[PDB]
Image (cartoon, coloured by chain):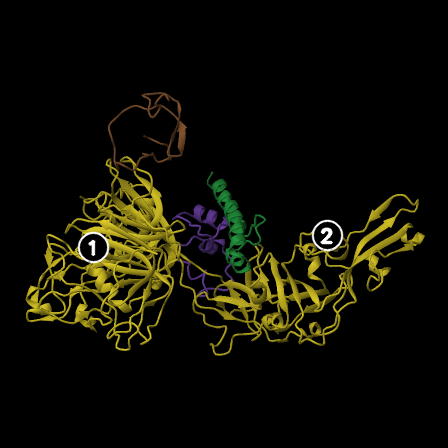
């Protein structure tokens, strides 16, 4: 990508996207400290498209 | 009653032998909804070639049904013998909001005789017979399927051209091989074509007489007959029950070729059908003259939504069960039989959660013994019990009094006994039944104005009851009594202002009023000090005569806390399994009466201790400090989104499970997002799941082709290229 | 916004359907649920717009 | 002793058909199935004929 793009991405505070996979980080098979609203979509029926 | 015709002559019956192992066949018939199989036409309306959606009772599309085959009985040589029959008489079924059938479906084909199957006779249509009713039970010989009181009877009689129906009481017969006899085996009916069904005089009573041979008609309340003509073409028929009585439907009456069923007839009977069975029958024909009969099928009705493809002639020609597949759901979403190609979201998997575990109690039994003695208070003298930390069985408490009124608000009357809470609160008082119009949570009576009020922030119940003559420790007031006034006079002695009672609290006038009201209309007054703001307190009351057995009232309310929920019903945990760990599926739970469902993880701890439950900003439980000294975190549960890839040009499809990972996927699954996924399995029964950068998929095959316009992009660099074009 | 609305009772006796079911007689149970459903549908409509 | 109003060819004159009622114009036209279901309706349950 570019040094500028990566600097930008580090400055951006957005939660990490799923799809490869992060399903197990919603679940007990991942850190207990996860607090992502991204895993909470599984409860709401919300879907993040790629 | 109904003119039943002549009484059966023989007390005796033809012997009936069960030959059921001969009757297995592998001729299942799934519903083809695209042929409109099993569709009941809507009542009182018709439509043009526009298509609609509709909900009503229908068979499930994937159901192959239950199949039965009628057969010839025992005969040998040149004569009729014993009734060799199937064991269908014992097949009692729960009624399931009606059913539909196929009749003659195997006609103009061949099969076997079954009882003497080596003959391989061609098969022909035969009409089915049925019995329905509100109750079933054992025959005096312990045999299955006896019916009680009045029952429905439906049977063709003699030739299929006559149909009869009845609502009657069966009468058992004491002869050899008959229902009251102890030589009874099983009920059966028969036809004897060697003398029955003459072409100059069909025997209209043939099957009625063989029916009567085992059960005499008695007390019959309804009878009907119908005219039919022969037709080997498959017929659809069915029966349902409504608040307007039982109704009959057939395709024969209106739609001989399309198979749509119309309501042919109705019945006056309002007795609910709780049970259903098929009546066995046999043909008495001679061993060299035997004829095989076509298979019979039945399907249970269900309250399902369907697309309906009406024709310009108003027949439904095609239909789609919305619930059958996610593909069917897609069609129902667009109200059409041809959705445009694309990728579309469909509902998520439910994730198959585990059966429940609990953390409720330890605690002691709730001491409800104060209720066992003394005189209960006048309504302004209330006595209260409040329970914490304890276990109970209120039905044992209830057994000690006779309750003449049990009602509740904001809680079912059953649930107040079964729910776990931070507290259980009971108020009790003496109360004659003569005053009962004034005891409700909404009452405008003087009892609620000045003696009691109940908050609506807590669920509550009310009990009116009386004391049994064997409760000698219970005692009663000289008269029942209450305060009917409680106000303060203004210091200038003209104006006066009422003091209504506070919810769940004693009225202020209790400080001047005597423990009972000595006489009806007694009143008292108190001058008030300048420290009290002046004026005169004034109060008065009324009485009701005492009764032979004490009458009582109770108010009951509950409080839900968070970490204080130690009052629960006595545990049912004995004879179960170790709790609460599974870890494991996202198991249903109750912890100290806090219901929920979710999965736990044995992680560290966060403050603060002894609050038990931990919550987020959205009021969702985060975790719990276990009394095994480990904090467990709660992740509630997860679900798996599903989407489909549909190429209508080839009419083919594939699916995507997103981020679930193929480590949690297998060729079949049960979580579940749909009752079946067999449409994918049509090709994917032979393939493993494939992981992709967007997600785990089925049926997409890694061809590694490069195409600049996929027409079904999956996002990123992914492509759902179609199988080679139409 | 969608997440916060999952906890938003509309004056219904509880924000949870299972909680309503375990607490009520069916004649009232579905009155509370219907009220809850209508507000939930309303948030979806606003969300789409 | 009456005007014989069983049909008109017609007029928006109010009608009643076995307890079904409304106002409208009638005109003899081809038949559509299913015959003997009486009332033909559209997808919005408006009577067609």
- Describe residue B230's horizontal placement relative to residue B465 as left or right: left
Q: How many marks?
A: 2
- Describe residue B381's horizontal placement relative to residue B282 as left or right: right
Judging by the rendered image, the residue that carries numbered circle 1 is B103
In front: B288, or B618? B288
Circle 2 crowding by C-alpha within 10 Å: few under 14, some 14–19, many from 20: some
Query: Which mark is drawn over residue B445?
Result: 2
Q: Kindly check if marks 2 and 1 are in contact, taking CB atoms under 8 A apart as contact.
A: no
Q: Quadrant of residue B123?
A: bottom left
Where does residue D28 sit, x and y in percent of width and height? 27, 24
Q: What is the letter of the brown chain?
A: D
Name the quarter where the C terminus of chain B is drawn: top left
- Asked if badge 2 and badge 1 are on a common chain, one would say yes
In front: B231, or B99? B231
- Describe residue B573's horizontal placement relative to residue B653 as left or right: right
In front: B76, or B575? B76
Chain A colour as displayed: purple
């Amino acid at each position: 990508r570019s040094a500028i793009e990566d600097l930008l991405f580090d400055k951006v505070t957005i939660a990490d996207p799923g799809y490869m996979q992060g399903y197990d980080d919603c679940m007990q098979q991942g850190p207990a400290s996860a607090r992502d609203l991204i895993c909470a979509q599984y409860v709401a029926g919300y879907k993040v498209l790629p | 009653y109904v003119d039943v015709g002549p009484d059966s002559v023989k007390s005796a019956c033809i012997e009936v032998d069960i030959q059921q192992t001969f009757f297995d066949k592998t001729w299942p018939r799934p519903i083809d909804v695209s042929k409109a199989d099993g569709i009941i036409y809507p009542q009182g309306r018709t439509y043009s070639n526009i298509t609609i959606t509709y909900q009503g009772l229908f068979p499930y599309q994937g159901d192959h049904g239950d199949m039965y085959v009628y057969s010839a009985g025992h005969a040998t040589g040149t004569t009729p013998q014993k009734l060799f029959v199937a064991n269908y008489s014992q097949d009692v079924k729960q009624f399931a909001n009606g059913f539909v059938v196929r009749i003659g479906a195997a006609a103009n084909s061949t099969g076997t005789v079954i009882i003497s199957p080596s003959t391989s006779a061609t098969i022909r249509k035969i009409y089915p017979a049925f019995m329905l009713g509100s109750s079933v039970g054992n025959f005096s010989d312990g045999k299955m399927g006896r019916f009680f009181n009045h029952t429905l009877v439906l049977l063709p009689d003699g030739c299929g051209t006559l149909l009869r129906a009845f609502y009657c009481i069966l009468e058992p017969r004491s002869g050899n091989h008959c229902p009251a006899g102890n030589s009874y085996t099983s009920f059966a009916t028969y036809h004897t074509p060697a003398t029955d069904c003459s072409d100059g005089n069909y025997n209209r009573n043939a099957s009625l007489n063989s029916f009567k041979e085992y059960f005499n008609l008695r007390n019959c309340t309804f009878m009907y007959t119908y005219n039919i003509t022969e037709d080997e073409i498959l017929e659809w028929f069915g029966i349902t029950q409504t608040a307007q009585g039982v109704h009959l439907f057939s395709s024969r009456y209106v739609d001989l070729y399309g198979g749509n069923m119309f309501q042919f007839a109705t019945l006056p009977v309002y007795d609910t059908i709780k049970y259903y069975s098929i009546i066995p029958h046999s043909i008495r024909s001679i061993q060299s003259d035997r004829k095989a009969w076509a298979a019979f099928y039945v399907y249970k009705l269900q309250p399902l939504t369907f697309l309906l493809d009406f024709s310009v002639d108003g027949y439904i020609r095609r239909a789609i069960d919305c619930g059958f597949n996610d593909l069917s759901q897609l069609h129902c979403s667009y109200e059409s039989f041809d959705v445009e190609s694309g990728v579309y979201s469909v509902s998520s998997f439910e994730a198959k959660p585990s059966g429940s575990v609990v953390e409720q109690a330890e605690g002691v039994e709730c001491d409800f013994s104060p209720l066992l003695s003394g005189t209960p208070p006048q309504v302004y003298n209330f006595k209260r019990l409040v329970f914490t930390n304890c276990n109970y069985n209120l039905t044992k408490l209830l057994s000690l009094f006779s309750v003449n009124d049990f009602t509740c608000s904001q809680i079912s009357p059953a649930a107040i006994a079964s729910n776990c809470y931070s507290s259980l609160i009971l108020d009790y008082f003496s109360y004659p039944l003569s005053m009962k119009s004034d005891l409700s949570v909404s009452s405008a009576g003087p009892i609620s104005q000045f003696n009691y009020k109940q908050s609506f922030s807590n669920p509550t119940c009310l009990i009116l009851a009386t004391v049994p003559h064997n409760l000698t420790t219970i005692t009663k007031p000289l008269k029942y009594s209450y305060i009917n006034k409680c106000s303060r006079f203004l210091s200038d002695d003209r104006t006066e202002v009422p003091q209504l009672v506070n919810a769940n609290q004693y009225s202020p006038c209790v400080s001047i009023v005597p423990s009972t009201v000595w006489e009806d209309g007694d009143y008292y007054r108190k001058q008030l000090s300048p420290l009290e703001g002046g004026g005169w307190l004034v109060a008065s009351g009324s009485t009701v005569a005492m009764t032979e057995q004490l009458q009582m009232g109770f108010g009951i309310t509950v409080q839900y806390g968070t970490d204080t929920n130690s009052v629960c019903p006595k545990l049912e945990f004995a004879n179960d399994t170790k709790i609460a760990s599974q870890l494991g599926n996202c198991v249903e739970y109750s912890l100290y009466g806090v219901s929920g469902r979710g999965v736990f993880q044995n992680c560290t701890a966060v403050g603060v201790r002894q609050q038990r439950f931990v919550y987020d900003a959205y009021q969702n439980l985060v975790g719990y400090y276990s009394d095994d000294g480990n904090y467990y975190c709660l992740r509630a549960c997860v679900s798996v989104p599903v989407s489909v890839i549909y190429d209508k040009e080839t009419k083919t499809h594939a699916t995507l499970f997103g981020s679930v990972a193929c480590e949690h996927i297998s060729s079949t699954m049960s979580q579940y997002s749909r009752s079946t996924r067999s449409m994918l399995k049509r090709r994917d029964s032979t393939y493993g799941p494939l992981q992709t950068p967007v997600g785990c998929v089925l049926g997409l095959v890694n061809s590694s082709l490069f195409v600049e316009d996929c027409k079904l992009p999956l996002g990123q660099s992914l492509c759902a290229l179609p199988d080679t074009p139409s | 916004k969608l997440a916060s609305e999952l906890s938003n009772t509309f004056g219904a006796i509880s924000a949870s359907i299972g909680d309503i079911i375990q607490r009520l007689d069916p004649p009232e149970q579905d009155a509370q649920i219907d009220r809850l459903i209508n507000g939930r549908l309303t948030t979806l409509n606003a969300f789409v717009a």
